[PDB]
Amino acid sequence: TIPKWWKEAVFYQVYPRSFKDTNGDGIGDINGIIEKLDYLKALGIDAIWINPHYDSPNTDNGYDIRDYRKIMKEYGTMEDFDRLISEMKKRNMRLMIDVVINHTSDQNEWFVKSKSSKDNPYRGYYFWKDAKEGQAPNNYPSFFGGSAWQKDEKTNQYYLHYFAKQQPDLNWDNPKVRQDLYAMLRFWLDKGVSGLRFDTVATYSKIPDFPNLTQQQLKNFAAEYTKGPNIHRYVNEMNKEVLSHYDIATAGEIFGVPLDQSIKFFDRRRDELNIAFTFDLIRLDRDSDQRWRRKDWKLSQFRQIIDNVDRTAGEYGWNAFFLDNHDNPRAVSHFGDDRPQWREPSAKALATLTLTQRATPFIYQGSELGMTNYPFKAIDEFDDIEVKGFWHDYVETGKVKADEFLQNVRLTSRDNSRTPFQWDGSKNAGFTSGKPWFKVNPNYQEINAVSQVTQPDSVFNYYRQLIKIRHDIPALTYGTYTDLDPANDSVYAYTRSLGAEKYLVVVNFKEQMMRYKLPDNLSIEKVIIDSNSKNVVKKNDSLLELKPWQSGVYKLNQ
Ligand SMILES: OC[C@H]1NC[C@H](O)[C@@H](O)[C@@H]1O
């Protein structure tokens, strides 16, 4: 166990575009983040991870980068960015930025040159291939719909894009590409950035000769794209030439990587990355083939995945833990119950388990308020290119009826987490003086930061209390994680232990009162915190009477 600031820190993720607008154009910006640092400090946040802040045409809201060395026009200036770093440092907060180097915008200078001719010096910065029998090079599908190969009539070849056609993949097999990327990383790291979150880090290495995927592989192509023969060689080379020269925290977004293989990216002995962003938990109820469709899940599955993720990190790796983010539905809607009667208690319950995992917790903007999914009705209400791609592939082809599709994407769309942050009860929830780029959830009159910061029993203040408790108790960061019963579908209970310091965490996932007798002669010394409960717990109790959605943290005897 090696203590590190990034294992003990409580991170907060800010999606700039939807956090706080300060110029009235309806788009959140860097000055807006700066304006709200005192709010985040009050919450108790130690580090902020911001989504892409670089010059971009926004086909994928920042993840299609046109110029890596320029600030996104809508977000502000380089001076604004340096000020954010300064203002955060003054508050002992650290900044983590998003590194998107699997692909660039098709407007990026490198691609503009690459596509201009087969002999351009930059041709090999991307993947260009001839048609196979007048068709795409192979059957690779794109995550955002259709083929991962886009035809360019000028040079009579197709280029590879795992994501949007406007996101051509960089050729990491070209040493010149790697060297230019490392130089770019240094440009940002030398500005004082404390962390890097690597976007789709496991797909940098492409499969030699691009052979077709089998019928089976097509059902989970994401996993096939993480099987490049040089991925670890490249991540480790990046560590040796760049990462190891700074005291930074690096997170790896390893979507598609089988859990068993994830440790190769985060085992500290391997000199690759630091913090694992696994997706086994957050996608537990998602179809792996029709990635927009959801299915029913049970608490036993949820906790069994957590146990597997914990065991996989083991002694040498380290995990992040989050229940939502900008690519997934809101935590309270997904894992809790967002109906008016249960939103606040279930949100507090999820906050309790989040802040007490043996992992670095990441709180997504607005979930500290209990923000919920957005009430989408028609397909034209979505901004997300991913849902549009699924719509084209599944509904426009007649494979799935529009109503069944909408029933599912209302619950799974990334856009559920991209509606503007709900600051107060004023027009557009105080997010902007103009017209928001994406509509504000009508529930902002009931759910907003101003209403909650001064109410001691608010969701915001429950997160604040839990963050302080985590900061105060080492066992809640480093303690061994033990699930008391992986097969229990009603009461989630586990202990966090560091020597003689042992804590119990309990969450009643059912909307009925539950009695829960502790196992193995465990008994309670004292309550640390609890939520949605008026029941009295006393010294030596070994049985808890749990109200619906009740959660709590207890110090155990011995
Ligand atoms: O860059 C492609 C994809 N990578 C993962 C990011 O979280 C998501 O927002 C983005 O669209």
Image: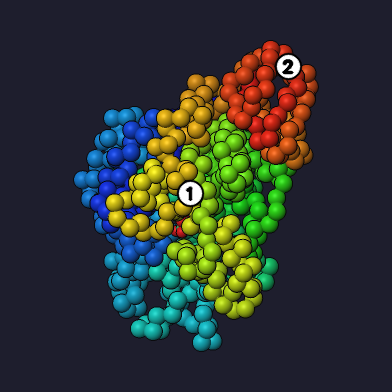
Residue 170 vertical position relative to residue 348 in the rendered view, above or below: below
- Specify the quadrant that holds the N terminus: top right
At 21% across and 45% down in the image, what residue appears? 79
Q: Which residue is mark 1?
A: 443
Local packing at callout 1 (Cα closer than 10 Å; few below 14, some 14-19, many 20+) is some
Tell me residue 201's x, y (percent): 48, 53
Residue 122 vertical position relative to residue 352 in the rendered view, above or below: below
Mark 1 within 8 Å of ligand 1, using the beta carbon: no
Residue 250 appears in the picture as rendered:
no
- Specify the quadrant that holds the C terminus: top right
Q: Mark 1, mark 2: which one is toward the viewer?
A: 1
> Mark 1: which secondary structure?
helix
Residue 498, picture quadrant: top right
Three-letter amino acid code of the residue under disc 2? Asp
Identity of the residue furthest to the bottom in this view:
134
> Mark 2: which secondary structure?
loop
Residue 448, picture quadrant: top left
Query: Of callouts 1 and 2, which one flags the residue occurring earlier in the amino acid sequence?
Result: 1
At 22% across and 50% down in the image, what residue appears? 77
Tell me residue 466's x, y (percent): 52, 28
Tell me residue 511's x, y (percent): 70, 39
At 33% across and 38% down in the image, what residue appears? 36
Identity of the residue furthest to the left in this view:
79
Residue 543 vertical position relative to residue 381 in the rendered view, above or below: above
